[PDB]
Length: 276
Image (cartoon, rainbow, N blue to C red; front, side, top):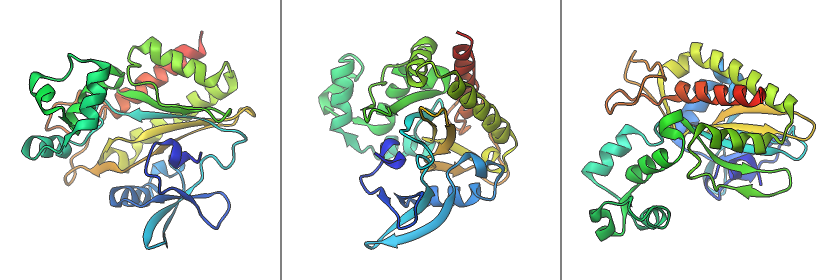
């Protein structure tokens, strides 16, 4: 499993010809973001982006293989933000819902009372409604991030974090993730602190709604730890000059992603975790 594969993406991910690279199905928001990020304070905080290549009539982001320097990577994909869908997707869901049966059924199996009577009748919900529900049953709403997935060095993968919500549950996931590796945790924390600092000055970050992106925590048994922001497929610029502080609550209209609330909390949780 490659890190794009681990961010739970396409089935398009592929090795490039060049060692230490990784092809991700190109998406325009992401290419744009990565390009900006390469010229941003956050350049170091995101996989190197080497541009786009064509293979098989499809465009791929040539990304640093974030896993490449790691020897048996443990990977945790942490979706950042109190909100995990664009406001534009919420708007589109109201205007023109694409009803998702699969997502309904996922809600219905998890919390049969969660779908409204109408959703029950449709056997389908909109993705944003699914995502909002996902945010509320996970830590996204309250903490501004959530664990999506873990790949362990043992090859195992889990995405079973959907109802990981409380600060402790999250802490526990991270605790299990880092497997007592204090160095990794410290590195993670240092990295996050640094990422936060970078975020807080990043021109890109202040100008973009960063939704659906993840912090990809990678470490290995050699205690290499990295964190990178990845998955900028839903990171989109704010209207000219408009900025987000990325902390204040999302209130439809303000495009606030709570990214930094998430990162604040994540840091807090990791910091709490480091002190256990």
